[PDB]
Amino acid sequence: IEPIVYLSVASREELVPLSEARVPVLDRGFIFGDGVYEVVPIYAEGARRAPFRIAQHLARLARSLKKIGIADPHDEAGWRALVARLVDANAAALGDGQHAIVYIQVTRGVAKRGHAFPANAVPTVFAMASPLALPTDAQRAQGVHCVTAEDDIKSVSLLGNVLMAQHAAEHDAAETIQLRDGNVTEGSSSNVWIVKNGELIAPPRRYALVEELAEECGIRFVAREINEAELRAADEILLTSATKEILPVTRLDDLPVQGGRPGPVFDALYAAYQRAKAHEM
Amino acid sequence: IEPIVYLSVASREELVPLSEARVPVLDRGFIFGDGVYEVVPIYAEGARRAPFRIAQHLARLARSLKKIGIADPHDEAGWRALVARLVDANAAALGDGQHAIVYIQVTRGVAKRGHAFPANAVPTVFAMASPLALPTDAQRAQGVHCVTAEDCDIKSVSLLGNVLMAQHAAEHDAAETIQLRDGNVTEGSSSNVWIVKNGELIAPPRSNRILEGIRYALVEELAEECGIRFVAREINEAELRAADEILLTSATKEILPVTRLDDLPVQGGRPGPVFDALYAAYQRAKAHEM
Ligand SMILES: [Ca+2]
Image (tube, rainbow over all chains, first blue to last red; front, top):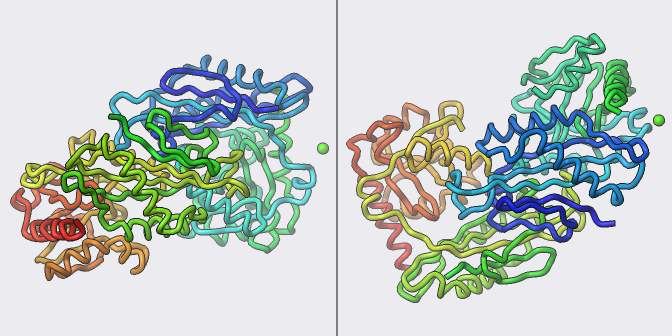
């Protein structure tokens, strides 16, 4: 019934029901958005559950922590055990055959409000395991609609992304593709790619699953600025994230992308994605 | 002894001791930095306490909420009342003559994690009243030291960038980091930056004149009372380093003179006449409201 979550505040840890998990009001994640997050997908085959790419996800988490000066509270083994206990404790909540997504957040901790790093704060850690519903077959068959709007760490200072996500909802679209000074940046909660003349293109920059899949398929990858015209004239437009896997974008601001049908680089990357998941299960 | 704070979560409200105030983990303030804040100075004449420019602080709070679509949980009177209950509840823990600063934070509330606005979340309100030590008579005589670094108009709690810049100042033994983007002055990590050049007061431009008037209202008022011309105009890095005076303002600092910059003196190293006048004007604004 109720989700069970993990919370560590002032070095005290507990797995508790969601309705009992609360953090002190002076936690810097709440006061300042001063924290980082990472996600790990957990794919289910009956009662067999297996994290996908947990090493690479945890390595990006350690990097985000260091980039903002926050003491990493666990080594890799400690993080994996924290994830395994959390997933175990939600076995009933989730149920057999149910994929999950694990969300991990670490903030600089609790102290008197002052912008600079406090001398003696201990990091807060929050994690939870939620049901994951992947995009449907129909969605992959039809593709998704994106809109555009004016726009290197996974921080929780996310107001910008919240606003662009709301913008996409208000426009009946799956995602807002952002443009800064005429060039593509990213989605509100996804990475954006285009295909042109058989070449996979992303904006200029490691966690790099999509590049690894492109390398596997023998698809050439270039990292360069993608301007608004090149976006609108793409052969294909793609979204990627832990929860979306890869989705084809077939409408962009009410105009069709190319023929308005998912293309072959999408197909190739999607199949290579699923083989990497089979490999791990 | 211990500060007493206001917390409203899922339509339940309380005044509780700081150490008893906790928010749900799925609050979007904690998960997404999805909220706004506003601070109100409370000045003390003995046991007498008075909020400074409460109407203007509360108008900015309301704008901040409207700007990012959070339903404002109070009209102005509701907010006024909330600030009074809170200050009154901390009278004893503050003590006589002790100035305070009220911090109000409003987030979009608690819900299942998803980026877009949740249908049923109700905004969370947190407020506290903390002792305020104004910059000393010394600090005003010596002036303060800023550094520069490489660097829009929402007062949000997505403040990681500001945190990093504040820490950069601390690491270089400086009171503030003055940010530059494209070679032009933006702002401090938690303060607004001004320069004086040939007796004219200059502030960086904002996105449009409306936002400039909201942001600069108090200093614009002080400058007018002093007969000091003010303009909102780009300050390039060389203009910043050649300034006659450099100034910081915020709710906690009031106005301060910057007399050193990246370890070099600002002119003589002495606070200057436009600072003196504005500071005096600031103090007459306080006295008047008190
Ligand atoms: Ca199928």
